[PDB]
Amino acid sequence: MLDNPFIGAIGYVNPDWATNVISQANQTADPTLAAQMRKVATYSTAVWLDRIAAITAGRGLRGHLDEALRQMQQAGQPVVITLVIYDLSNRDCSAAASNGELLVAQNGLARYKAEFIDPIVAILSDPRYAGLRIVTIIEPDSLPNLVTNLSIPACAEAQNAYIEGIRYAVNRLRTIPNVYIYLDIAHSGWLGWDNNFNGAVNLYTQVVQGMDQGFNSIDGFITNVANYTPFEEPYLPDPNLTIAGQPVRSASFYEWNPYFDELDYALALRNAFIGRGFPSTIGMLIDTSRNGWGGCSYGRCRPTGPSSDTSSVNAYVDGSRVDRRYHRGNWCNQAGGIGERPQAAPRSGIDAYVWVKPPGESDGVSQPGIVDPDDPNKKFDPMCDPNGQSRYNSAYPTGALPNAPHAGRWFPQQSEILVRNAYPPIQP
Ligand SMILES: [Li+]
Ligand SMILES: [Li+]
């Protein structure tokens, strides 16, 4: 088993996502933007298994793996395909409701094992796929809730199902020698504060220690999945820098969080886990699909230096940060930009920047009253309301784009914004 499956392999290109991108390009008036959209279709994005039906619907898990085999044969190089394992019972427990089909009180954990993990593992175990490198991102938006959100009944009730579900998933996947396993561990805007950071290190250490292979059960962690947090905040490199008698991390946008970006956060976690007994062979992934923050939106353009306004902490930080969101918890349908293209080992400790969330796919429908005919479990979330306030802090707008289709469906307007705002800009 490789130290890093992204070294010496080319990323899987999902033809179903790429078809949507190319269709968008053909509907794009601006010839420059259209050529950029066309180029985006050539990059590697992850295949999400977000419900039991995803295993067989359309080309299905087998179909994507067969396609990966074809790309491998054509390229004469190993292909690395990324899969997102995302169907825990009481999924996304801190949200008032989730699109996830399984509930703890309705045999959720048992069905997670028997109808979701087991058939996936049976497919991935097929000797036909032995030559691929298969990366599995384990359960976004799960464990970090057990650090910060246990006051919420759906999270407190989900504790064992999350722990036992994730242990089961990893234990079974570890029986397949070409599967590389990365646990999702949120992003800096969730677990950066000292108490959350230490609580997460404790929690994940306990979860992994209880797996069959202990600290050898996983290959690393991933941050920023489907989020927009920059990998680097180059004009705020020092969270303790004094402006107007106060450190810049005291700004309203950060609320004393010592981590402004995913590189610092991911590497700090990696060192902390190594300190707890994880082998130094662990590596971190960062989802850079939508965190470039080029172009202009939310009343600002990308900064090109520290703010000249040193009159207040907030003025300085707000003029210096590349993350332009109104509030760090604004996760739905943001007017961001595509980030760094997928690339292996960009810094020591980082296995790769990857695109897990596929750019252009919606984070959620933008108003209630509209049922998804193809998924009865998809539901409107107020964080996607373009006319609403953040639920995490109602002083701030959601920043969500209007006219969004249900989660996972192609979102023409956001796709154009994401490409136009790409950083570095897309090279057609
Ligand atoms: Li490694
Ligand atoms: Li930094």
Image (tube, rainbow, N blue to C red):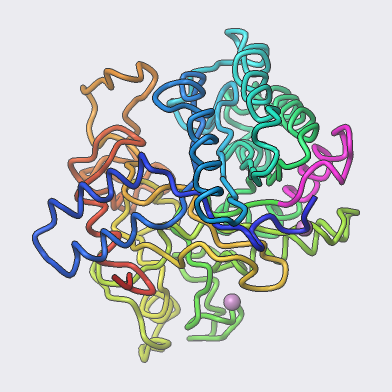
Q: Is residue 296 above or below residue 161?
A: below
Q: Nearer the viewer, residue 290 or 327?
A: 290
Q: Is residue 28 above or below residue 371?
A: below
Ligand 2's image quarter is bottom right
Q: Residue at x 33, y 43 (%)?
A: 361
Tell me residue 35's x, y (percent): 22, 65
In the picture, the quarter occupied by the C terminus is bottom left
Tell me residue 160's x, y (percent): 73, 23
From the viewer's perspective, is 217 left or right of 330? right
Q: Nearer the viewer, residue 184 or 281?
A: 281
> Where does the magenta region start and end?
199-220
Q: Is residue 402 above or below residue 245?
A: above
Name which quarter of the figure residue 366 lies in.
top left
From the viewer's perspective, is 214 left or right of 202? right
Tell me residue 238's x, y (percent): 59, 81
Helix, strand or loop for the magenta stretch, by majority:
helix
Task: Kindly give the residue lying farthest to the bottom in the view shown.
Answer: 308
Q: Is residue 81 above or below residue 280?
A: above
Q: Nearer the viewer, residue 202 or 176?
A: 176
